Length: 106
Ligand SMILES: [Pt+2]
Ligand SMILES: [Pt+2]
Image 1 (cartoon, rainbow, N blue to C red):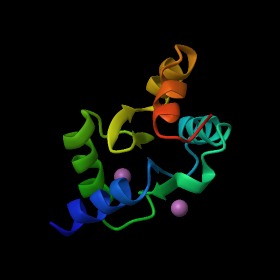
Image 2 (tube, helix red, strand yellow):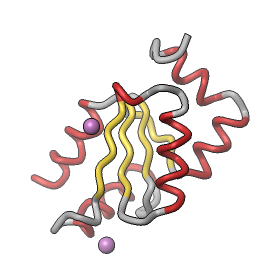
Image 3 (cartoon, rainbow, N blue to C red):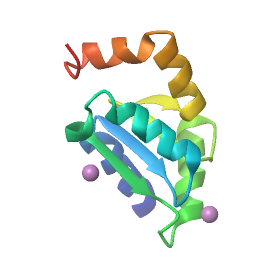
Image 4 (cartoon, protein in one colour):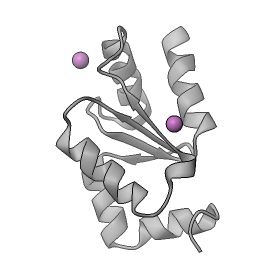
């Protein structure tokens, strides 16, 4: 239960929640895209590889999203998914619409 509660608190306390790991190019790219929207104040990045419970965290992220890979991206508890999902939403205008509805971008 403790792992699930830990992941949940990260997702609930931060509007933009990103689970990543060390030296992960698509993590870095996703985080960079999000920071380009000046989301820093409402973003939290958790490195789940530097964690004794990495497998449990990944299994729970898969239960929540369908995939165990990082990056895993949540916006106001909604599953965005991975960096490719973020790029699709960004290119098609859905990311900006998300952030507008949250008051995060004018
Ligand atoms: Pt943070
Ligand atoms: Pt691992």
